[PDB]
Every structure is written in C-alpha cells, then in structure tokens.
Length: 170
Image (tube, rainbow, N blue to C red; front, side, top):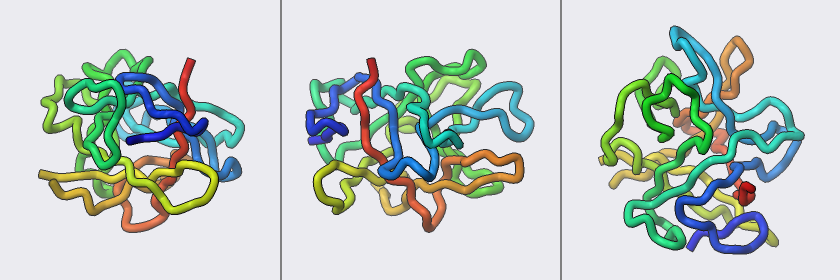
C-alpha cells in the first residue's frame, strides 16, 4: 500500500501535495500556460522551493479506501483550471516527448489510469517515482524538462526522474 510523508496510508480519492524529496530543486505541482493554450494546461513543478503547490487528488480504479502499491492511479487537480473539462492529468506526445497535460475534452478512463507510483529505496521516508504506463507498459519515468520560458514541465524523459513525497492536504 501507498504511504504519505507522515508514515500513514494514502487515502483513496484524497488530496495530497506532491512534494520533492529535497526542497532546493523546487516546490509542489502546479499548472502553467505554455504554447498555444488559452489557460494553464501544462502540469509543472513550482519554481518556488518553499511551496506546497496544488493539492492533487489520488485515485485508483476501484475507488478503494487505500491505494495498493503498484496499482495504476489517476492523478488530478482538486481545484482544476476552468478550461479543463476534467481534472485528470493525461500524457500526450509533444515536441518535448510524452507530456503531462490537462484536456479541454472529456477523457476515457484508459486515458487517465496511466500512472504508477514506485517506491525509491531511500531511508526514514517514503519517496516515490512516477511511472507512465501504456497499453500494461510502465517502463518510463516522469521527469522534469524546463522550457525557455522557465517552466519545469512534467514529461517522460529518460532521466532526471522526479521523486515525490506525499503530504496530505487539508
């Protein structure tokens, strides 16, 4: 089962801030306006090391009490951008490669349940890596690739995987 930054089980359907392991390389997850988007449709990591970012909802397919380790998950904004037709993060091929975005169209479940948290080996705390799966292929990790406008975009990059500790929102 999944564990949060306080050693407790992650509540299914619950909201969490997805924080870095180490502060100095930025804060929580947010949205951003990039390219030809009329609103924040690009999921990014805040530049501010201090911050919590957006509370993110974590759900599995069976809307169960907890989320089984190695279970597919959907991740979405609790307070999503108005132009988004659903709060769920989605992966789409882009110039920077598979990018985590929001959509202006309704999405099918097969299109949202494409993430898998994976525990990283570190010591007194539960740190995760984010796996992007593709129809059952969870072999790519989500990482950061910063654009020339400064946005730390969430995309599938073959390195610099992002690591996360889950802090229960309130």
